[PDB]
Amino acid sequence: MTVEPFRNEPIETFQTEEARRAMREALRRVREEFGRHYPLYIGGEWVDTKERMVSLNPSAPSEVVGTTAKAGKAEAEAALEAAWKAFKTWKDWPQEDRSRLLLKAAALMRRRKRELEATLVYEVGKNWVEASADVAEAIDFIEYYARAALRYRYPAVEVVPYPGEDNESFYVPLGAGVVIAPWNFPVAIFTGMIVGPVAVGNTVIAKPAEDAVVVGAKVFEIFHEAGFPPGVVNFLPGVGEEVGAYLVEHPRIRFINFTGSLEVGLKIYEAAGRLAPGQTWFKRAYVETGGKDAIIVDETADFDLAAEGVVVSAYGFQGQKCSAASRLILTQGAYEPVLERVLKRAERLSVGPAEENPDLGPVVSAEQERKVLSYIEIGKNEGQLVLGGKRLEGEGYFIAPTVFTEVPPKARIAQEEIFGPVLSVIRVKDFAEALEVANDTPYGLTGGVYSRKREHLEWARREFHVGNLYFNRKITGALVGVQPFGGFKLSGTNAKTGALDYLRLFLEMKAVAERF
Amino acid sequence: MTVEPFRNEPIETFQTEEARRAMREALRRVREEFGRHYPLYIGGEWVDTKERMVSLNPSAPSEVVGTTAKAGKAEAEAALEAAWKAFKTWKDWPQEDRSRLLLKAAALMRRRKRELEATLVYEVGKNWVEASADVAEAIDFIEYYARAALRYRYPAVEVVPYPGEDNESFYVPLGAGVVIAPWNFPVAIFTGMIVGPVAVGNTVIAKPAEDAVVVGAKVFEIFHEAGFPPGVVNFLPGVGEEVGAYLVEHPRIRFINFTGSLEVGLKIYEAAGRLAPGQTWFKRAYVETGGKDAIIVDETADFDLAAEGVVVSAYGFQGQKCSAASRLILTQGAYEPVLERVLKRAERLSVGPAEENPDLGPVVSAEQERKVLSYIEIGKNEGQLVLGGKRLEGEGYFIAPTVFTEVPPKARIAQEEIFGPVLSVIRVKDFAEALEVANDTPYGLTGGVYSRKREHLEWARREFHVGNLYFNRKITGALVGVQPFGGFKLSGTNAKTGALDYLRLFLEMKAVAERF
Amino acid sequence: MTVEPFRNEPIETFQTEEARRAMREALRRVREEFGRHYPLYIGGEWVDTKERMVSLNPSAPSEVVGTTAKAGKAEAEAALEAAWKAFKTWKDWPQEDRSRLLLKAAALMRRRKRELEATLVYEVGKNWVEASADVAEAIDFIEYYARAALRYRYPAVEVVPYPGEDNESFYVPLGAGVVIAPWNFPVAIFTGMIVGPVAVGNTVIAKPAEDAVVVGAKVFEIFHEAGFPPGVVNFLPGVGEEVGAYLVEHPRIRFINFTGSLEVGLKIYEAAGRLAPGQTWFKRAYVETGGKDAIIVDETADFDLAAEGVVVSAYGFQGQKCSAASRLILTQGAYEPVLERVLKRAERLSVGPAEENPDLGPVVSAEQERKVLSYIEIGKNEGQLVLGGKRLEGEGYFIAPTVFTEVPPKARIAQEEIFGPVLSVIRVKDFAEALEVANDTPYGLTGGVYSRKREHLEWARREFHVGNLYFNRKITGALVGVQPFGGFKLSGTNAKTGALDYLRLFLEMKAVAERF
Ligand SMILES: NC(=O)c1ccc[n+]([C@@H]2O[C@H](COP(=O)([O-])OP(=O)(O)OC[C@H]3O[C@@H](n4cnc5c(N)ncnc54)[C@H](O)[C@@H]3O)[C@@H](O)[C@H]2O)c1
Ligand SMILES: NC(=O)c1ccc[n+]([C@@H]2O[C@H](COP(=O)([O-])OP(=O)(O)OC[C@H]3O[C@@H](n4cnc5c(N)ncnc54)[C@H](O)[C@@H]3O)[C@@H](O)[C@H]2O)c1
Ligand SMILES: NC(=O)c1ccc[n+]([C@@H]2O[C@H](COP(=O)([O-])OP(=O)(O)OC[C@H]3O[C@@H](n4cnc5c(N)ncnc54)[C@H](O)[C@@H]3O)[C@@H](O)[C@H]2O)c1
Ligand code: NA
Ligand code: NA
Ligand code: NA
């Protein structure tokens, strides 16, 4: 290795005066720039368009945080041309050179962390720590993938020798692909899905989520300053079902890296399986979708520890996480003790403008507000509302921490991803039934168990069918490198982000033999 | 390791009297066995049906090598139930135990080698050495995967540690899947696609090609004797578009391992991308399809060495290989010298009943014969026929080694996989044009270059876009472990058989963290 | 690895106000609980007895620090049954699961360090830092053995392969054994001797020293909360020659892990060699006994550094350490300079109630006081008393730092382990004679050399025959992992604690071959 061993970027807690001062300064700089317009980034240059995308402040939707260009089919085609032209030479860069480029990007991002964090606060309503964790994760993806990519360098395949011959197998990148990202982790996931494929030689056309186009543009300002060759990375903010679908169905798109809703992921995976007219390969599509994550608590657990972890997992970033605890499964002996503690903690949570660092900011948009409120109405007919369940005052999309109890395992609110601050509590007889209820959903992303009984924990290790399982701690915030992230079943294709295996997904192998 | 390092099973040449004696006895016994009936194998037992599949001797089609039961939807459902029930416990077997079972199966197959080779001679018309290579490859897959699987044993993932926590990532098998195999390597590929997934904990429903159902049943006799638990491996001979498609489209099939034509592979990949009613996961489909493989020869090559390798690559097993040289690209200075040598060697090839151990046996079936002859008629109007191009006398499906020259790069016979003893010779100006022509097809499986010029060889290593490239030697017969096998573009999903990476395709990862 | 690399638990120095405040709080909580009664722990539950054991405060013996149940033959039998019943399934736990259980225990102990330290202060008279070092060492044993155990996981043995066979060798635990511990390191050694064997699959019946039954019970409160299955670890406070001897001589005790006096160790080793009626194995007995440790100082040493290290080594925890410097061997040129400095430092040492953090607390009991005072009387007839040698005022067993000079190498005080604050100074001619005198004792545990001459240090490295040798530093306080601890000759069986080799002592090997 030529760099220090990987370490996770510390997540700022803002406990010091200097950290708070630095954040206030960043917040001011960011809002003073609310009038900025960010063009598309294609072939190494910023290119503007006639139409535009508008980004609002979810804590004050009448306030615009910025606008960006809007990519249509023509811009998608221009991006494709630039990406394939660039691939021709980018694929030949020594891996050491590509990895150093990522390391430079990581250093530049680290120097602009407060700015990016402040942008997350205003654009998608993350409180201070949720924003810092997001940016820190993005830096982690760059640092981790830069190092991981070297593990695949020419010629990396272990083969069996043969007399009188040289047998050499090695990996090569696939080509130009499209990255379609979500709005909930607009810096971290957006960055990771882009730099992983790019690190090993692929080129990318990135389509940020409509609600986070501004922060996505700032990430590209970093890529531009880092010096990625023209066409290696392209920025195409636009409408998902328009430019996103166009690229997904295109015969010249080699792979698709998607993170988002199951509904969209299903369409993308299906489209990826079709041979478009003139297409000359089998497309690879990686789709990480939602989850309906549960935390199980039995009668042997530390109830206070459990209540704390549950509240953090269910309401962090207003529950807008694919890893959020949306189900709380309690065995009979743990039901009362835990529910009472969860209710007491949850009722003390503050909700308000994200910039004031409340426990909960607003949900991301009017559309999300509509969906969450709709599920709350459905919940009133399936379970018992015991806390919250109301829109709070203000133009911002403030929704109160909500709790439904005595919820049937098969209830819609106990099966469908609400993606809001809504927790469904389910009462079960014992641990075995708790596991049965935990597994009985179409998903399998994250899960947790609070218990002191070793046999229950190890039992869950083997049978709680989720890609990321946590014992006696929160089930959100998977750290790059430490906890490969990705689920089972309808939670996705199990493309483990922040892990060595992730990069293999964007490579193909060639075996060359020479008989002397 | 607890066993000797992997070594490839020696391919018998039958040059010694002992080898000839053993082979003659095996052929005689298999011949005396003609007409035997083999049932389906489901849940650990042989199960017969009313309908049947008939397997003819391509060297004398009036002779029935044998018959097998025929699986329909009911049998597919019974196999699904058995496979999923078996998965529940087979997945928990220590890896060391599963690997030992494969090693036992390999030992049993090795002891029945002559019999299996003799069955290939009669059922699919392979001469003696082609049959021996097929069986040897099958043994290699078992031996190799048994060892490779141990590299993924619990807990195999390299992760970054975190203070106060245990972070453990490990692989787990996917579940029950279907294996759909071709008739050209009915022991090797059939065995490989089955034991790879099974080695790491998956269960399989195997669908042999219609023309090779008897040898497929004999492989299952070996699996049964080895002791695989009931339901771990199931044998379902039947019609591809019927029972095969039924399993591919089934909501309860977890993965599909397919090797066959591009036409079928395309349908399978598309179907796999769809969420069948009630399906709870994203299906994984691996499809290794055909190719239109070329051997390039420039003016610096050893023309005699090249001619020999071209004839072997083009006519081995009647050109019925996904790796067969179906295109011969000659630079101007190599054109006359190489073509004349290829023609002289090819015109001396013997063609006759496979049991006689001729250079070429018959093509596999009446329909394959019809298709090949049809392509020959097409070729007569695209290029210049300079050798063969006719069916020979006799009931068997004998086609003479055929050569077309001055063939346009875009001609149908220079683009479409004929899968018969038909070689298309293309004359180009220089090595640069040779590479352009070689890459200009929808495929990318195998390729070869005969040249003494280092710069041309290394140029090809970087730009001859095929998954398996060979220099100054034949382009067929990839050895397990030595040459990871799999292509690019429409030649498949690049699932490299006989390589460590192959098993990862049938596993998913789980990350479990415990905060102490 | 799935956890961070091993690091030694920092030893608290109490230099900060917070640390002192935390200790005072712990001391108060502990003394407020002096009236507590601690039952035996058998088969996962606390079981009381009719008779009891009383623990006194050596700094104020009229004050009881607690009482515990008292195990007799019946309780020993109940413990044996529970331990063997538990072994049947505990031995089958995956090593990863057993190691995680130890890690949990370590985390729980770390959270109760001040409480345990305060208990050591009041129960066995350790000053603040001696108590913190003891607890830190215990945590270290758990953390170290948890990691070390994984190095022996199935199948760990390196063997030579053989054609046509799978040859697999692996380790398995021995069964149920007894741990008999000393009172001087009642948390550290008690913990280490228990968790090492348990980590790899054995079950244990632990017999704490009579003078430290209370702190031993608290360690078991930690094991109980951690969740060790019923019967895996059992707590049997009681009389050594009663319940201890009973278990040692029992035909159903598989191994004995003992740390204590040579007198007892000799009896245990002899008894272990006998086949008790009905016994079906050869018992393994590990006995780490005393020492008569010397520090050599030559004329080239840093006399002030040497005097400091000598005082620390001889009087730390009142010299009640198997590693304590009880002999000071000085070459002619170093005699005066070093002795004068040692006397000046030693006369400034405070002695009093342990809770006030004096340099020396009291010896552990009336019996130890009697022994130490008796050796002081013997010393007056063998050497010259130059410092201390008196019982100090107060009911506590306070003995003053003592120094005897011009002591004959063969004198009883220069040969027998006093286990008190008594240093014997021996004058020798040169370094060679210093080594001869150092080696001429029945022991061989710890030793030290203060010298700047490389040739003398390296000479000692090769010929100063002790298991743990230290140059230019104290000879006590061996750290887990850094300095494998254990001696030669009558200092024991050389079972190196805090080292990879320790766990091998509690395993046996099986070799299984399968001919395919
Ligand atoms: N599994 C994970 O790792 C993970 C992590 C973060 C978010 N998520 C999921 O993301 C969802 C929230 O994100 P969202 O609301 O942005 O998701 P979404 O599916 O509505 O949109 C995701 C992205 O796809 C685009 N898009 C929309 N329709 C499209 C179409 N037909 N074709 C192509 N692109 C299209 C959008 O513009 C956006 O860029 C939740 O379901 C959550 O569980 C998953
Ligand atoms: N890439 C490789 O490794 C590789 C190796 C060997 C053969 N092949 C290819 O295989 C082909 C020759 O094999 P073949 O003639 O048996 O191929 P094929 O595609 O016609 O049939 C392959 C298998 O699929 C079944 N099948 C047919 N239609 C199906 C459907 N709709 N759904 C599901 N299963 C269906 C058949 O019964 C048989 O078991 C050639 O194109 C050759 O290049 C590829
Ligand atoms: N070598 C080492 O690692 C090491 C470390 C610490 C202490 N020690 C030694 O320990 C001694 C001080 O400890 P102690 O006074 O508790 O020792 P001890 O030998 O008097 O007693 C040790 C333990 O054995 C039990 N015991 C006593 N007689 C027994 C018998 N006949 N059969 C079975 N068990 C019996 C006691 O109850 C106690 O649990 C010193 O000699 C010291 O050198 C050795
Ligand atoms: Na916004
Ligand atoms: Na046939
Ligand atoms: Na005491």
Image: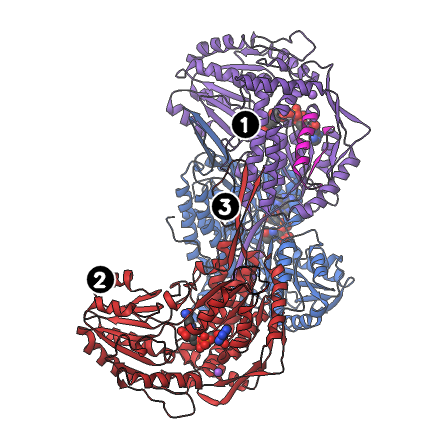
Chain colours: A blue, B purple, C red
Residue extending farthest to the right is B50
Number of on-image labels: 3
Give the residue pinned by disc 1. B445
Identify residue type, mark 1: Leu
Q: Is residue B349 visible?
A: yes
- Magenta stretch in the rendered image: B214-240
Q: Nearer the viewer, residue A57 or C306?
A: C306
Q: Residue at x 54, y 16 (%)?
A: B17
Secondary structure at numbered mark 3: helix
Q: Is residue B164 visible?
A: no
Which x, y percent locates residue C103? 52, 64
Would you say C201 lies left or right of C135 here?
Answer: right
Q: Is residue C49 above or below residue C506?
A: below
Q: Chain of mark 1?
A: B
Q: Chain under label 2? A: C
Q: What residue sits right under mark 3 in the picture?
A: A196
In the image, B363 versus C445, the foreground residue is: C445
Q: CA distance from mark 1 to mark 3?
A: 27 Å
Q: Label 2, on which residue? A: C454
Tell me the amino acid under the disc marked 3: Gly
Give above or below for B79 relative to B386: below
**In the image, residue B289 lies at what x, y percent?**
61, 28
Asked if ligand 3 lies within 8 A of label 2, the reply is: no
Which circle, 3 or 2, is nearer the viewer?
Answer: 2
